[PDB]
Image (cartoon, rainbow, N blue to C red; front, side, top):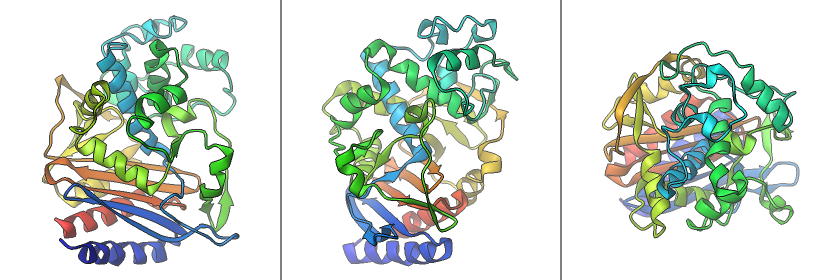
Length: 359
């Protein structure tokens, strides 16, 4: 209930997590009764002894897919695209017969038929990207199986913005970031903000890898703890969001498009019915399960966003580990940002422990 109790609950979980996982720096935001509480620990840059602050930028990895889903939802609300539209409507160059029957819905929800996890490192331009998709051989018919893939949701983001006439980063900045006042959220970090951009660590060493094709769409957002708290607030309850297409896009990203066991696939967001057993989300986050091709069950028509849900997303990069989770029915949420990638089951367990103790 009190700020001191919230602080005690958060510190009791995060301090031993950082010690056990050898995390150099972390920033956490808790949304409790719709209000944000911010916490920072450790170092953004070990060698220069820079501390984590409320302005520190962390790489979100796959949490970037939530921004992709919402921008896609906003495009639907504008009347620019429809999830039922064929992929070929936005990329007429994809003449391959295997692309007939594949819709934007399938790209957004990993159900196109076995698109690969990543874009190959040698595919470095649009013609090479076209050749890659043109020669891709599906494993299953569209809608049969869900197989998590950056080449799937990455292409959804790229195509969703085509009617806008803007690049993906520009459409994301104008349509999502600026209206929600996310002033410390970037895809390309400007030179003047490099001083706040944390270093990611792997095996005790600073790591940096240049971005590849579709990185912005699938995995390229960087954000601060304050903006991530604002992102969770807006996604939990968009009633204050003045821009209607964005309010509607947020709601569309939490619609239930497919059922995969106990999980429901949204646009970027993944949801489970609330209340639930902690083991479902913890075991569910293990990469062996998360990356598995599993039968997908279409929800006809998509079920509108359910308030009684555990809505979440994990994400990592070579040097970062992030996790966001929220329960709209309880006006309760958490953001966990770290400059070391650590096991997903460990993130989910720590988030569950904090949110269980707060409720």
